[PDB]
Amino acid sequence: IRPTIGQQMETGDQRFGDLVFRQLAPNVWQHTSYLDMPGFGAVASNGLIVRDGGRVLVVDTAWTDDQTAQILNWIKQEINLPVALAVVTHAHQDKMGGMDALHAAGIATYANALSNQLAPQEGMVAAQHSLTFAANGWVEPATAPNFGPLKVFYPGPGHTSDNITVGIDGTDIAFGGCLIKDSKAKSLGNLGDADTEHYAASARAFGAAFPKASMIVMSHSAPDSRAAITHTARMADKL
Ligand SMILES: [O-]
Ligand SMILES: [Zn+2]
Ligand SMILES: [Zn+2]
């Protein structure tokens, strides 16, 4: 009995080691990893895995190198294709905590130049390559070589100064990372590094950048429809 990962994922989300994987589209999966907070519920973070022909692309590490190695184990087991590159979406632990595991696997890594400046300071590792964004927010194509369907956009400061977002061309998906929370959220999570002045405008800019994305994927909520964007901006208004 040898079903494909897609065939297997019709049963629903799959637990794998300490992670959870969910198929969002035929070649797109959400990875979820958890930060144990002793005496409290574990903090979930989501990223993406994209199968782009004969290669795999990753958006965001897990919280730790070990959890990120578990992501790579899942990819080997279920997809059985090489991972070419990863894009990581700001210098917080949930997004860049596992860079060493990616680097050791021979994966080329990319982040906002600003993320690369902020990370070492915080005990993390910079990505190997720096993305530069035009004033309009779109990544300068020369700094994002061979990204396949990934379309990278800097929406402005919000959840952090360096937060970036990623659309997946040929799908209904755009990844807001930690900038966006779902349409029922009671808070924006930890705002300790947030730009409270600009957050709402940056959430709006993300929505305007990916107007055809009907599935919004987020770090700290399950996927939602576009109402998540204005809900997030409403929650962020006049912080
Ligand atoms: O975060
Ligand atoms: Zn963050
Ligand atoms: Zn986060």
Image: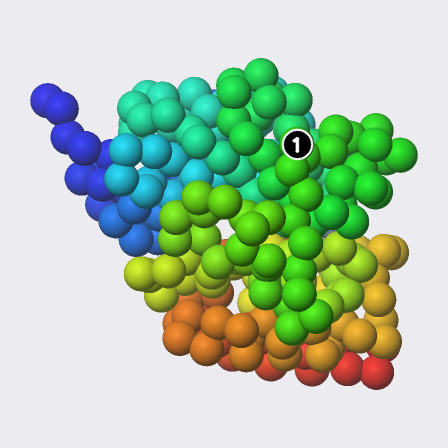
Question: Would you say residue 107 is visible in this rendering?
Answer: yes
Q: Is residue 191 above or below residue 124?
A: below
The amino acid type found where label 1 is placed reads Gln
Front-most of residues 215 and 99: 99
Q: Position of residue 61 (x, y in %)?
A: 59, 36
**209, above or below 150, in the image:** below
Which picture quadrant has residue 122?
A: top right
Q: Which image quadrant: the C terminus?
A: bottom right
Image check: 192 left or right of 33? right
Residue at x 59%, y 34% (from the top left corner): 109
Instruction: From the top left corner, tell me how far across and down residue 92 is, in percent.
Output: 75, 43
Question: Residue 210's x, y, as percent?
Answer: 48, 72
Pick whichever, 214 or 7, lies toward us. 214
Q: Which residue: 33% across, 40% down?
A: 51
Left or right of 10 in this view: 234: right
Q: Residue beneath label 1, please? A: 128
